[PDB]
Amino acid sequence: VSKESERIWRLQRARTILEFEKMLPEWLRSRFRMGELCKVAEDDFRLCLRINEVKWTEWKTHVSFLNEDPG
Amino acid sequence: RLKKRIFAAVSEGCVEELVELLVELQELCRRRVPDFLMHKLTASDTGKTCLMKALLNINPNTKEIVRILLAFAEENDILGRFINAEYTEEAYEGQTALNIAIERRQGDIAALLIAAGADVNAHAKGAFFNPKYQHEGFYFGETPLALAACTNQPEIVQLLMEHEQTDITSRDSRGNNILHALVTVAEDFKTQNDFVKRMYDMILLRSGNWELETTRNNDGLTPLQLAAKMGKAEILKYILSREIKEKRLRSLSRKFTDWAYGPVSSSLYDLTNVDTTTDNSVLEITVYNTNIDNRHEMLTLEPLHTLLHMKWKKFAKHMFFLSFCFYFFYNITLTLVSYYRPRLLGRMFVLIWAMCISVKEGIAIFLLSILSDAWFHFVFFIQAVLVILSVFLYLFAYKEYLACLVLAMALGWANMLYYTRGFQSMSMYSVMIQKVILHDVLKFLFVYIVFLLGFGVALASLIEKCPNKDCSSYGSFSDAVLELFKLTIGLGDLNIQQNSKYPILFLFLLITYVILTFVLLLNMLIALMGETVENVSKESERIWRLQRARTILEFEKMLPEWLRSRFRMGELCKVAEDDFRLCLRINEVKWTEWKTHVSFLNEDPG
Ligand SMILES: COc1ncnc(OC)c1C(=O)Nc1nc(C(F)(F)F)c(-c2ccnc(C(C)(C)C#N)c2)s1
Ligand SMILES: COc1ncnc(OC)c1C(=O)Nc1nc(C(F)(F)F)c(-c2ccnc(C(C)(C)C#N)c2)s1
Ligand SMILES: COc1ncnc(OC)c1C(=O)Nc1nc(C(F)(F)F)c(-c2ccnc(C(C)(C)C#N)c2)s1
Ligand SMILES: COc1ncnc(OC)c1C(=O)Nc1nc(C(F)(F)F)c(-c2ccnc(C(C)(C)C#N)c2)s1
């Protein structure tokens, strides 16, 4: 139950978040609507969500980009 | 629209001919001066140049790209302020192209940029490189040497230290030099393969001198005290028991074998900033810091363990037994004064010792997590306060002194735990000082008050106003709350006759309350027990060792200066040409590592 607690809390929170998001008026949802447009290719322009993660157990090297300039 | 073209041609790298033609066009536009060229060569939003964008995007043709860029920069006498350019944004301020070349593990281009004249002291003084807390940003040391050593690039660390203008004794914004940074980044037993230990040893031997290790950051900590502050058990074990076997760097060691004959070997350990004779030593920091949860493994290191054992066996055992005896006779006198209360030999030794304890523990509190280590200070102070208050109320004409006197007697017999925590019979109390006081008892109290109030209302509501014992002990809300409390205290009795219009609903709610309070109590019970008896015995032994070290250091602070100098662990030993550092001798016998003994201070053992 140590972990089962986290399981049940996560499930209840997800269901609560989704039903609350359903309760809002459409204009409020359009106001919140996380995710920003991003050009990915010639004409792709998809709604992307930026996720800055820190994996402090890293041993590798990264060389790729879309906007190499750190945001 | 040429800036974006140069940046795209330099980031994509699909062909260097694109950037070659674009640079020809740029030079043509420049002929019709340096500030214009680099304002067209940088991004005004962050300050990044095309060199950083070329190194941030490594591709199979990036070495030729940086060669082309540096050739074009030197062909215009601008390469000085172009290879040394740095970000301007608040988050990544100070980051230059050498930081990016090292963070991308590009050694060849790094040598190229250092040969071209990129200053090797560029401090990445940004809010991303100096995070407020870890896991939000990347702190390596704000320097190319620290970045090369933290990312496990000993080739670049050699390339950086063999350079001429490098500052090995450079201190970043946090005050850290390279060694504080290495201590900060060092992870664990087998997580980072102990490469930080390798870099620490290599950088300390390269610059063989005591300045890197005797340097205090902005918190007044040296790399050794910084390994003590954090829970870096591996780096602390390395620095403390560090034996250099080279002939020139022997004075850098902190441990010196001087004695080996066969398997027998008597080794000296250095106790300069370790043996509580200074401001705050590895011993003080390791014992008193309650923010690592690793003192179990750091207090068993090579000099610290024997230092604690020696202090104990030398004076702390005697002081501890003497204080236990004094408190035991204080409690016996208190018990005999409380039993023979006047409803005569000495009833003031109680009073003088109570005032002594109150002032001592009060001064102890005044100089300060603080409910687990410094817990007994509060209860000893409260007991002494109760005693002196009982005396004051007794010499006044108060008959309410007996309550405080009996409470003080009982609380003193309870405070007798502090002396008997490592006796295997007061184990559960010693560990539930930590377990139950944290949050489970307050969660239990909140839920129990909710149960009590709700069921008090639910049961008092069900009862009918009756002509004046009312046939019901669940009368007003307070009587129902009292009956319920007495119930969970095993003081009551449930009867089916309570003068209700709904006796079955009343009985249902009463039994529901009983069962719910039992569930609550049993949750708290299995929490307080949490047996795993092997692990709970580890916990009790660990608590005993931690408090033993803590009280050893407490007792060492009470002695005067002359008694401390008369105990003074550590024999003075000459370890170099003229070093003469206080050490601590430890004899060992190893029957496995058979080696010819060429490092020693004395050739004649004994
Ligand atoms: C080794 O222990 C002893 N040996 C011989 N005699 C003794 O007492 C005569 C004792 C002893 O522990 N006495 C105590 N006194 C008090 C005081 F409240 F008065 F402070 C105690 C106390 C304090 C706070 N919370 C509780 C709990 C949670 C248990 C409740 N309810 C109890 S406990
Ligand atoms: C935080 O809890 C509270 N705080 C303040 N007041 C309270 O009640 C006054 C309470 C409380 O728990 N009330 C309750 N109501 C009812 C009910 F009759 F509705 F079923 C309870 C009940 C009765 C019988 N079997 C169960 C289960 C199925 C769980 C078992 N086994 C639950 S319990
Ligand atoms: C209807 O009863 C209940 N309903 C719901 N919850 C409950 O408890 C959570 C209870 C209940 O009986 N509680 C109790 N408390 C205490 C106390 F320790 F405080 F004295 C109890 C007690 C009293 C006297 N001798 C003992 C022995 C020596 C047997 C022990 N051990 C225990 S009994
Ligand atoms: C005063 O406490 C005692 N003193 C001396 N002897 C005792 O044993 C008889 C007792 C004692 O515990 N009596 C109890 N009866 C019951 C009941 F289930 F019937 F409600 C209890 C109960 C209530 C709620 N949740 C549990 C769980 C699920 C945790 C279990 N298991 C058990 S507890």
Image: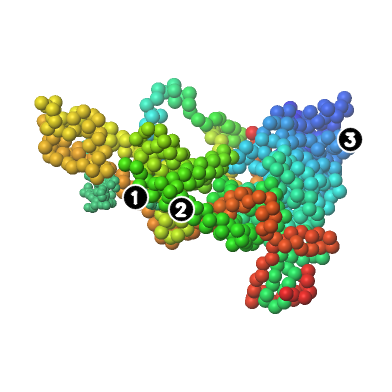
State the residue in front, B532 or B285: B285
Residue B8 lies, in percent from the top left, at 71, 36
Question: Closer to the observer: label 3 or label 1?
Answer: 1
Q: Residue furthest bottom?
A: B262
Q: Going 85% across and 37% down the picture, which residue do you hit?
A: B79
Question: Closer to the observer: label 2 or label 3?
Answer: 2
Q: Quadrant of the C terminus of chain B?
A: bottom right
The label on residue B14 is none
Is residue B59 depicted above or below B599 in this figure? above
Residue B134 lies, in percent from the top left, at 61, 42
- Confirm or reject: label 3 Cβ below 8 Å from ligand 2: no
B502 relative to B247 in the view: left or right:
left
Q: Distance between the residues labelled 2 and 3?
A: 88 Å
Query: Which secondary structure, mark 2?
Result: helix
The amino acid type found where label 2 is placed reads: Phe
Q: Which residue matches tag 2?
A: B329
Residue A30 lies, in percent from the top left, at 46, 24
Task: Give the mark nearer the N terminus: 2 vs 3.
Answer: 3
B174 relative to B350 in the view: left or right:
right
Question: Closer to the observer: label 2 or label 1?
Answer: 2
Q: Going 68% across and 75% down the picture, which residue do you hit?
A: B264
Query: Which secondary structure, mark 1?
Result: helix
Q: Which chain is disc 2 placed on?
A: B
Q: Which residue matches tag 3?
A: B77
Query: Which secondary structure, mark 3?
Result: loop
The amino acid type found where label 1 is placed reads: Leu
Q: Which residue matches tag 1?
A: B525
The amino acid type found where label 3 is placed reads: Asp
Marks 2/1 same chain: yes
Marks 3/1 same chain: yes
State the residue in front, B354 or B63: B354
